[PDB]
Image (cartoon, coloured by chain):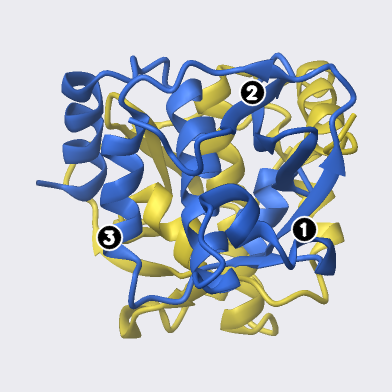
Chain colours: A yellow, B blue
Amino acid sequence: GPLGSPTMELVYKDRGFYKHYGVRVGNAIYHLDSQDILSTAITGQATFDKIEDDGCWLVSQVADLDYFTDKYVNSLVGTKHIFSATQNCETIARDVFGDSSMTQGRALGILGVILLSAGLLSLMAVPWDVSSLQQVYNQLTRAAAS
Amino acid sequence: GPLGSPTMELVYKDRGFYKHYGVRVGNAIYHLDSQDILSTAITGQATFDKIEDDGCWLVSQVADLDYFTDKYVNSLVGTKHIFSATQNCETIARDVFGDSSMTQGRALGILGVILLSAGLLSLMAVPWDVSSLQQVYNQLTRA
């Protein structure tokens, strides 16, 4: 089902070792501004930026991705997250989620869930159907020592 | 090369979709206490714990992994990292690195880099030889 506002498009660039997702709204693309996904994870700091579409992004079929992302949207509602934004992201909540009452902060958290979920699932080559997504989610939430 | 003390081993359990890594010293295993890497990444909070070996861990051949992990350790020396630990890990520096003078924080940063690197590189199906690792390093860091 839908991830956000009526015109938001999940897009990506294929960087070979990983696919890098963003969201396109009109000619604006919102995405994480660093390719160093390992540094991002280790430091707990990720910054969104808004860029112009360069014509080189591909569109993702969203399929049932929301089944998976909703689990984290719900589970990390009252939880500090790692996402900040540049000054160019003033209207991200409205653009991406269609909700002017949502704070920028809350929008960054939800969008960061979506983009990291898409990127991780792509790395795992997991299709975005409910069955496949539930299977991955079960392994992610399995007790670490088990 | 070696990643730590002379008896330290890189170990994992295979979850199919990914491998969950830890480091072993004797029958003590130090690992992240959640394998929900999304929650870990989104919240910027990873907690090490120390468990007993159940005999069901596999040993990784480390090859040249330290070539890659050392680069990240060196980049994040004067840099906050996300790794904390339960109190069971008070002796991780002496156990894992063989250095009682090393701070717990420094030990956790190094081991966190190693475990996340191993996990990510495995997902990428990258040989842990220097040439392969230099190629993915260059892509990650935009050199």
Q: Which residue is mark 2?
A: B18
Badge 3 marks a residue whose secondary structure is helix
B61 to the left or right of A30: right
Label 2: chain?
Answer: B
Task: Tell me the mark number nearer the camera, choosing from 2 and 3.
Answer: 3
Alpha-carbon distance for marks 1 and 2? 22 Å
- Return the x and y of residue A90 as percentages of the image width and height: 43, 84
Q: Which mark is residue B74?
A: 3
What residue did someone put label 1 on? Answer: A73
Front one among B22 and A81: B22
Q: Is residue A16 above or below residue A103?
A: above
| Chain of the residue under label 3 | B
Please tell me the numbered disc located at residue B95.
none
* Residue type for callout 1: Val
Instruction: Give the foreground label among 1 and 2.
Output: 2
Query: In the image, residue B43 lies at what x, y percent?
Result: 67, 66
Q: The residue under label 2 is which amino acid type?
A: Tyr
